[PDB]
Length: 314
Length: 302
Ligand SMILES: CSc1nc(-c2cccc(NC(=O)c3cc(O)ccc3F)c2)c(-c2ccnc(NC(C)=O)c2)[nH]1
Ligand SMILES: CSc1nc(-c2cccc(NC(=O)c3cc(O)ccc3F)c2)c(-c2ccnc(NC(C)=O)c2)[nH]1
Ligand SMILES: [Cl-]
Image 1 (cartoon, rainbow over the protein chains, first blue to last red):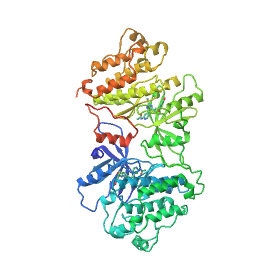
Image 2 (spheres, protein in one colour):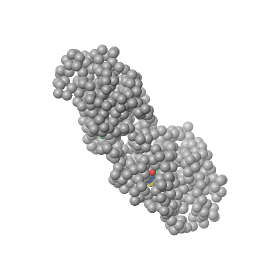
Image 3 (cartoon, each protein chain N blue to C red):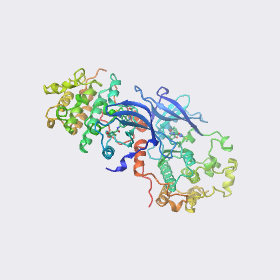
Image 4 (tube, rainbow over the protein chains, first blue to last red):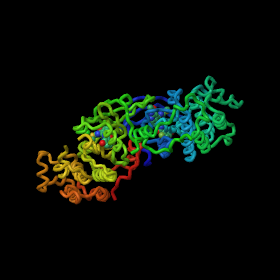
């Protein structure tokens, strides 16, 4: 209750469209505290309608859980406004989502960065599992970039709260992430922490291919059919077999045979200490992590919260 | 000092966008920092300093900026970056609320007692840190206290007066007569700063010529008791304005006294009607959006 602020329409205004997604439309907004004349920039996500007749109460009940997460790699829901539409408010991060970032820096992202992103994403998911929360829609598009050295997972639980209409699960490119889903989730709508591990594997594939679309050209209606016959996402050219084997274990049919998020943290952090042994990238060396000076600059301006330190090289 | 705490910016990676204000030390701009290889523009605050009385060496300007970048305290502004061209430009975090002097004036009819007493607590905490680092401000005033949130203020521009080279009505008498600047003379200006807050931004010795302040202090005259101040508050202010600098209070004793008074604020400030400190919900909203650095909890009422 003390973690979630209930906003009124009178104290915030949408001032710029930022993008649209499977869950709603993102705006750059301004919050005016009562009695003040300043405008604080915020981020606002106006959600699509739900398929269920959800009352406000329990919409607020899931928002209370969204506002209760405390981890450097999980987005905390800061505020909510229940008007005609449901509007979620969080801190504005000028870098956007990680999927767009790797697409904008495809020839300039080094190994140290890619491996550290996989560590931080697994750290966030491991926290969500500790909170016994299942994301259901983990993907690079749902990873937000606070700084290039600090990423955070967002939109956990929005898939279960909003839901998706039955026709989308059998349509092409709908509000259903078929190409990120575990097979048990496609066949029987079973969502666990272990199906999150599957989507984590696809998310890592997204980063290592610098934002390539998974199963591109393959119809979503045939994904369960090709997965049943043993076909998986191909090995990215920069990935050694050690990295590719990790991805393949998250896509195992037996959900309990997939790795745990706490074991994914350990394995990727060991690889981050010696990044050029596990990722082969052209000119990888001159793609350093930032100096102490510049990160101290990044942190003082944009990231005054504390996080783990990014895993350094040998 | 770790040189790693001061980033030297170049003109191409930052550009001024809007004037925010002017002072005796320079002009304040709202700026945007564009990181190299980044398509983002981060809002910053930029202070371009005016010409120094006597022209200092570039090493010295750079040597003192390293000290300004070395302070680590929730109530002292840390210098984040500098750009040394023809002019000197200082870069710090952008704070949308501005200075405490304008804030207390704009809320002349809205300010509650817990804000005023806690602001005094925080200013003394910032000054005590500067005293611990043996840095002398020389120009502590309400205009030089910045508002990050209404519950969080920070001191700025320490040492700029000595680098650039006159607030007569904020200075201790030893500073007027002989230009003696100590942590003790900073205590004098702290009292005037508190008097500013308790009068909601009133000008000290308004209508009195600055050239006559030296005589008015020597005959024992001081700033009057603010209408909302009980004598406990006013006695603290008068003790910082004692002629004997060694008899003035120390910043560590000002922290304790104002924190005691903040625990029962309406027993020490008599205000007609203002607004209390924010809920836990509104406090974490302010901080999750705007203020994520480490602070001690603001002193609440018993
Ligand atoms: C790529 S999609 C996207 N959505 C968002 C967004 C916006 C507002 C709120 C939320 N979410 C939650 O509040 C929430 C939901 C839950 O279920 C669990 C927990 C929660 F906290 C998300 C962004 C985003 C956020 C901030 N700044 C930017 N900046 C730029 C340049 O785009 C974008 N981007
Ligand atoms: C007194 S007027 C004023 N100056 C500044 C300012 C701006 C940039 C740099 C500095 N200087 C220092 O940071 C510095 C100086 C030192 O010597 C020691 C250590 C230091 F950190 C100051 C502001 C200010 C700052 C941020 N946001 C706002 N927002 C609004 C709405 O006005 C204003 N206001
Ligand atoms: Cl100034």
